[PDB]
Amino acid sequence: TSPNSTVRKQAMHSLQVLAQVTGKSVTVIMEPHKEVLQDMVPPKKHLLRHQPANAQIGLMEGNTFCTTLQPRLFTMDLNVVEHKVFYTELLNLCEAEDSALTKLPCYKSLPSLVPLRIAALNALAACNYLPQSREKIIAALFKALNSTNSELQEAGEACMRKFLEGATIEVDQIHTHMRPLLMMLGDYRSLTLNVVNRLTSVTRLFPNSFNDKFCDQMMQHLRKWMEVVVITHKGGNEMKICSAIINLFHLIPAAPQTLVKPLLEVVMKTERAMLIEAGSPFREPLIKFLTRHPSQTVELFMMEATLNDPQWSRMFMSFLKHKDARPL
C-alpha cells in the first residue's frame, strides 16, 4: 500500500517472484502477515478524501492487488460499513465529473485526475464477485470505455477485460450502454478517431455486438472519409480515421467476405488518386482483413483481367510479399 509507486510496484513484483521461486501462492505467502493490511484493505481509519492523492492511489492499487489474487486474501463484504464506504467512494470517483473532483482540496493540485481515475476503475473492476454491485460497476466501466481521453479509454478496456474474467455481462446490457454511441455514428462526420477507437475496443471485448449492417454502414463511412482524404490531398487525422476504420473490419467476426471487393476498390481508388504505394497506411489493416478471407482475395486477384491490369497485379504482389500474408 506504499504511497511511493516504485516501492509499491516492486513489492508486488517481489511477492510474485517469491511465489514463483518457492512454488507457493501469493495468498499463502501473504496470509500470516495480512494482519498488517487490516487497517488498509479496505481503508478504515481515514476517509480517502482526507488522504493525499498518492496515498489514495497506493491504497486503491494495494486493494486491487489483494483482491485480484487467485484465492482472495481479502473479500469485500458490502454489509461491513467500512467496505460500503470504500465502495461508494470508488463509485463516486469513477462517476463524478472532473470539475466536481477539482473543487475537492486533495485533488485540487493534481496535474491530471486521469491516473486517479484509472486506479479507481481498477479497484472497482476487482469487485466482480459481488452480485449486487455488478450493474453499477458495468456502468462505470462502460463510461470509462467511452471516455474521450485516450488513456482513460485504454484503462477502461483493460479493466473490462479484467472484469469479464470473473463476471458475465448480458448482450442487452452491452446494447443499452453502447446505444448513445451507435446512434451518433449514423453520420460519417461523427467518426472521430476516438469514436473508432471506442468501437474497436467494443468489438474486441464483445465481438458479437456488431453485425453485417454495421459493416455496411462502416464501409459507406469509409468511402466518404477516403473521398475526404483525396480532396484534402488535392488541396495541399482523416488518414488515421480511414486506417482505424479499415482495422475495425478484421476484428468483427460478422464481416462478410463480400466486403473484400469494395474495400479493395476504395483503397485502390484512394491510392491511385494520391499516387502512393509504399507510404500508404491502408495496407497494414487491409492485409489483416484479407488474410481472414484468403480464398476470396486470391480468386479476385487471380482473375485474368485483374492479372492483366498492372495496378491490381502490383497490389497483389505487394500483399503476397507481406509477413502476415501466409494464408494467401
Image (cartoon, grey):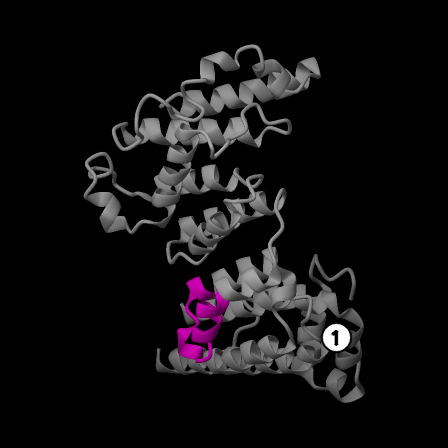
**Residue segment shown in magenta:** 178-195
Q: Where's residue 48, x and y in %? A: 31, 30
Q: Is residue 283 visible?
A: no
Query: Where residue 213 sits in the image (x, y, percent)?
Result: 61, 79
Q: Position of residue 80 (x, y in %)?
A: 45, 29
**Front residue of 242 and 82:** 82
Tell me which residue sits at (44%, 79%) in the image: 188
Q: From this viewpoint, is residue 24 visible?
A: yes
223, 280: nearer the viewer: 223
Q: In the rendered view, would you say 165 is above or below 50?
A: below
Residue at far bottom of view: 305
Q: Which residue is pictured at 34% across the width and 44% down the height?
A: 92
Please identify the quarter of the rendering in which residue 89 is found.
top left
Q: Is residue 72 magenta?
A: no
Judge from the rendering whether residue 64 lies leftward or rightward of residue 318; answer left or right. left
Q: Quadrant of residue 20?
A: top right
**Residue at x 57%, y 23% (from the top left corner):** 73
Q: Is residue 261 left or right of residue 162?
A: right
Residue flagged by tag 1: what amino acid is it?
A: Thr
Give residue 298's position: percent from left, percent from top: 78, 75
Q: Is residue 179 magenta?
A: yes
Residue assigned mark 1: 297
- The quarter of the displayed image where residue 29 is located: top right
What quarter of the picture does the C terminus occupy? bottom right
Residue ranking furthest to the front: 79
Asked whether 221 or 96 is in front, the reply is 96
Magenta-colored segment: predominant secondary structure: helix
